[PDB]
Length: 156
Length: 156
Ligand SMILES: [Zn+2]
Ligand SMILES: [Zn+2]
Image (cartoon, rainbow over all chains, first blue to last red; front, side, top):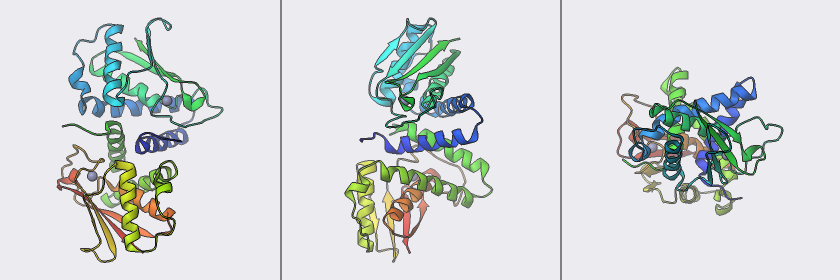
């Protein structure tokens, strides 16, 4: 049962349980984890190579895709398993088969809960630095029984 | 200024700032960080090699020192810069010149605040799993301008 980055996932699991206990609904929990991601995305953008490797003018869905690839290589030393520009019209969908956030997590009866919504917030924060108004949510999470984690980035 | 594990560092930084805003004294903030550490410590003991690589019967000061070395190897893939059972008789002092928690943090003021007290709690929790009663506190932190981070493990 090998775990990568045990400190990070233990701290995140703590935040997830705290969030679930301090909110009234699954949707409120999703939004609170997104807010957490937006708050830590500020430091993650400025304190890492992301602010140096990304360009100032992010205009198109293809530019957003490139920006996502830069985030992934800087934070996780890999590419996303898929970036899908066509299935959700007006969106960019990102797939990760080995998400760091939910390793070995198994929640039942919580299919509406985006366990890894912190990453939705981190992407919204980075796009906001580029003055790209975006809405990001998690479509699927291995934590709730899916085969991969998938986030949906809508430029809106 | 390159940072190791930027997601962990930023998430922890969020926790510290929220803790400082919610507590009524620096020592209360210190205690909240140690309590977070104890919770993290439970997860890192159950979900890493620490439990499989450490002795079951920890009886001497020398045994506690070797346990600390194993924690450091598993969590950080390094040894502490110093483990001191000399300067503080009855306690064990751990020195880390490149602490993960406070990379690039430079607080102003905050005398008495241990930015990295989360690791005091992790240590206290692991020792507790080994039936070793300890109180752990941070002597100094690079976040408040020291050149090193030092934690003091007091036995009994
Ligand atoms: Zn995930
Ligand atoms: Zn430190």
